[PDB]
Image (cartoon, rainbow over all chains, first blue to last red; front, side, top):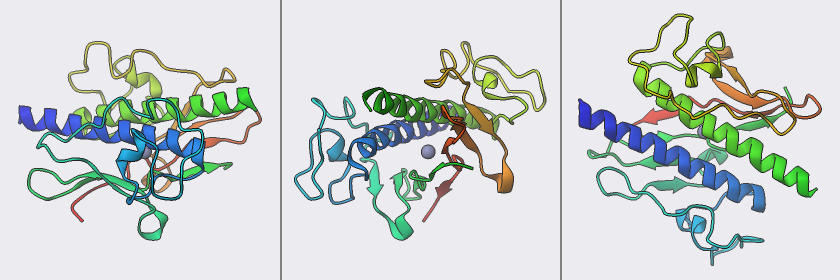
Length: 108
Length: 108
Ligand SMILES: [Zn+2]
């Protein structure tokens, strides 16, 4: 379907945009925001510990996108087994999840 | 270092932007470009099979970024164990790698 394709593109684009903002937060802070801090950490410095350092004016993203069905995206952090995920719940409660965003390596 | 911090932010930002473009390519084609097709497949329809379907005007990214030290970013796809990575070689040949970008799930 056409609407379905467009919705899928929005979900994937938003989740990767959130991923990038979360990675910029982590470069400044050495860790991602926790689920307790939430994606809100990307727009205002978190009140819950661990506190952010050198928080940039305006935060890390211009706005927090919502999914095509009007649900906020959700953050699992630090997550089970230290795997950080960002997901949409979908229209039907079958989550579309961008998994283990922290899987980066230095060296081969 | 100040330059070093800037370079690191650029590498992470670029690699995530490339990740997003690759994911959009995959939504249209059901698979990522292969290493043989390369990141070039994000800017112009790939000459090598498997050919892209209905390739969009302007491709998937305005232009390919280069890393802070003048090297192209590199794509491993489909990769060892089907794990797709995008990386910078670094100034010193110690790669900074955004790993297993295809790790997404449907359902919990
Ligand atoms: Zn990712």
